[PDB]
Structure formats: structure tokens, C-alpha cells
Length: 245
Image: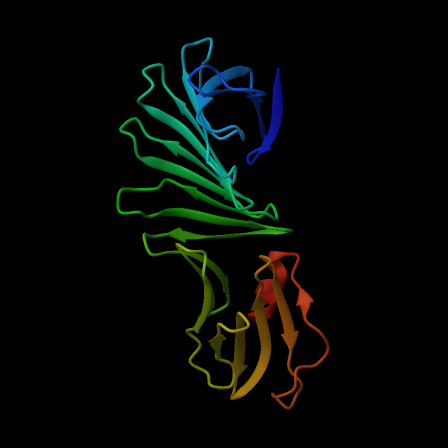
């Protein structure tokens, strides 16, 4: 006898239609094969639900007061050793795995558009390996405490896409080419999230890193001043490499 409330993270809670003698609301949810249950001071679906798997593993679902965030935790049978945690809100999900001593070892962030950041072998200094999964291609790189750095190399050029803890993007380019005729340099404009590449004192192309997690490339005219045509949305890693030739 309930009202169903849809929740972040592809879950559903049933909140009792009315409250008990203590004024509390019963909550029921199903996750995988498990019915979780709980009680709440609120009537909207928020609160905490708990369940025990057939093997005695402990699961807890916490729904924020405004329904904007859910946290799904899987524990061992003691209910204290965390195995997995999945937090979903504002259109993204973060799924973590934890080591036997309690610390995050793996993290997957799925953005509202389905692109992902996959972090593997996270260490105590906050370092690890990083992958950005975009529409059509994947960027590989490293994680540190300060940033995620995705790297594409072509010839003597290294392009580095840096993502802050907040998710702020900046991009840099370095070329080890000693020839001034051919060495690439680049300037970053954070206003438009645009890296402008220059060769031999003329601009050659703009690489835009969109708030929509895509990359576009636009060429300059021979004059090195006017952009010509229109920006091309990259759909394969080979196109990024081409932009760095």
C-alpha cells in the first residue's frame, strides 16, 4: 500500500501511503534480487533502506532528502567492510570499488551523456591510470591527486587534456621538433575551451573541447587569421592525431 517514487541510479522506492504511530514512513525498494527496507521521517521517498543478501552480504541505499542523490553501498556480511559504492546525482554516476583495507581502488564516472572516466589501480597518493570513453573513441592517460591527464601523441607532438577534480578542462600542447618550419605550439582560451595551434607563426587550427564532451577541429585560412569552413566533430582517435600532424 504505497506511492512509488523514481530515483537517480535506475532505482525505485515505495513509500507507505501513510505514517506509523511514531509518525514514520515505511520504505521498500528492490535492488538486483534484494528487497531493502527502512523507515523515514519524511513522506517523499528519502531515507535509508537496508537489506541482507542470501549470502549475508549487507546492502544499504540512502536517498537524499530532496531525492536528488542516491548512494548504494554493498558491504561484506559484517556490514562494515565496504565492497562497492554507487552514488548518482545531477545526471552522473560514480561507481567505486574498495580494497580489503577500505580504500578506493577503482572508480567509474558516467556522465549524463554516457561518456565515462575510468580510473584503475588508484594508489594511496591519489595516482592511477585513467581512460576517457567518448562517443566513438577512447583517450588514455594518468590520474594524480590534482588532475586527470589524457594524452595523445603524434610524431614529436604531445597533446594533454587535463581535467581538474571539479571537472574543469584545460589543454596544452608540446612539440619536441627543433625545426621552426614545422614545430607546433598552442595557446589555450578557457572562455571558449579552445586550443589554437600555430606552426611557423601562423595559426593552423582550433581544437574545441566542448562542455558536451566532444572535440571539434577547425582549420584556418592560408592567411592564419580567418577560420575557414566550419568545425568538424571528431569521431575517431585517428582524427585527433591528424590534427596534430
